[PDB]
Image (cartoon, rainbow, N blue to C red; front, top):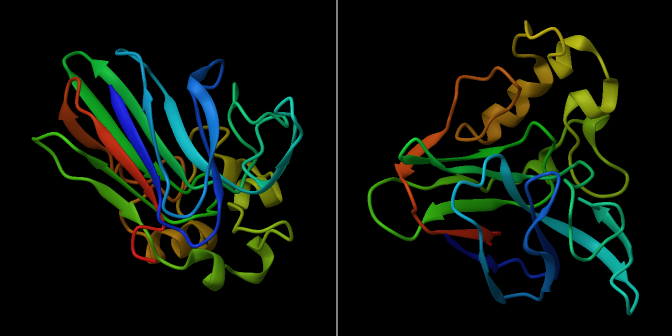
Length: 207
């Protein structure tokens, strides 16, 4: 499946793509403002995620640090990134279908649109100014808006017991972006696409 990842932000981002125990394609690449990077993701990929990382420095071997979404200091991500990270999430060819969503469960760093480029389903978007509006206690001094689990480590925010409800913090993300997951048990905003769709992830789709 092809994912065209496009940076419409006015700032550079370093895109990242992983399924948590492996890179997808090269796993990561710098995208200057306006650049597009097309990756190939193997059919059947379960639990893949794409995100942006901001304010990164890499040496000549691809080792360094990002202020948001760092994946163990690598340019080419092999694991998931450090919160806060707006997440494009997808499981492909799952009994005939693809499933996509955007999630703020790990916080928010960069706005995103995640849309099929082939027929038969709608895209999802979380493009509101969540960093500018972020509640004081969730603001990440590093950049971005953390989710309450990352900040407070409680069963209720982390849904550790499987039994949690919405909270004042989850409701903030859900108010600014109704079309993304705001906590683990949020009412699903997952979109079902034809098996083997192709997609485009656009960072800063409205700015």
